[PDB]
Image 1 (cartoon, rainbow, N blue to C red):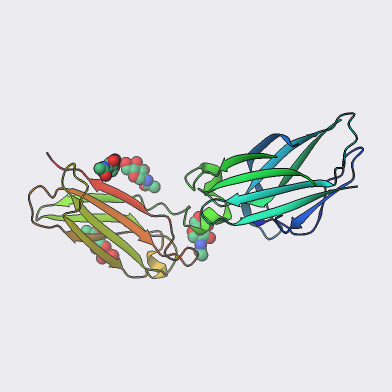
Image 2: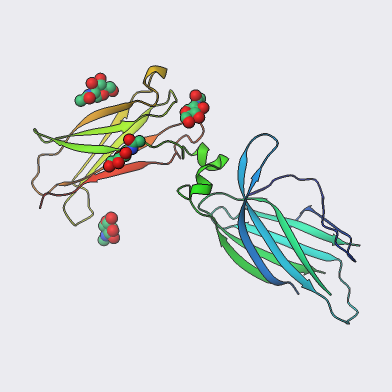
Length: 244
Ligand SMILES: *[C@@H]1O[C@H](CO)[C@@H](O)[C@H](O)[C@H]1NC(C)=O
Ligand SMILES: *[C@@H]1O[C@H](CO)[C@@H](O)[C@H](O)[C@H]1NC(C)=O
Ligand SMILES: *[C@@H]1O[C@H](CO)[C@@H](O)[C@H](O)[C@H]1NC(C)=O
Ligand SMILES: *[C@@H]1O[C@H](CO)[C@@H](O)[C@H](O)[C@H]1NC(C)=O
């Protein structure tokens, strides 16, 4: 959770002069949050929360200085606030909060001196999220298209397409019985960082399976370690089903 730009924004409308800026975190109607995408001057692409709500005034003489817009990231408890500062119906919009893929947010509006709604951002498999800067940093553009072939002597041959980075990969084999989810075997295979010559080429690893009847469901997972996502890159898997 962050602001796209931190300078004060002009939010003025006919009959209402308005400024909005980040503030220290201290009635609104029709609070709505849409997912939008912002392209930056630096050439990046971020998912943003497009937040809107209505201020309805009546004949009532009232002291109204502004509004506080609060966004809480539920996984980290990161909270950011912006304060609207004033001078029948006015619709307010704020689209400068950058959000993270696959995260839930709680949005709150308070008139100063309330309404709360939650917002869930789709993961990096969503076609529009896939091309954002955060998703591409998680390796969203790489498609290994992992395939696992059963070999004659209780071995598997795993094939996968490498990306274009000189970083290592790991293949994690976890074996299971047909239905029970307690593993009967586990093995990690280190794939050395490829040379630029093997970039975008399809490589393979041969895995040796545990010789145990019933230990027949083999999950094979590839984890890349691209410099932009370290231990947090998107992973892919294929599973060999039991021939039972
Ligand atoms: C990925 O694997 C599937 C296997 O059925 C195949 O249809 C598809 O064409 C493969 N993709 C590429 C890029 O070769
Ligand atoms: C990696 O491959 C993609 C293929 O679309 C390309 O856009 C990108 O520029 C390549 N990155 C590097 C560092 O060569
Ligand atoms: C066992 O693993 C499968 C994985 O697809 C899952 O659907 C199922 O709910 C799991 N069951 C238990 C008891 O963990
Ligand atoms: C498996 O991959 C290695 C490169 O990592 C290659 O030398 C070998 O020939 C490939 N094996 C098969 C069966 O294609």
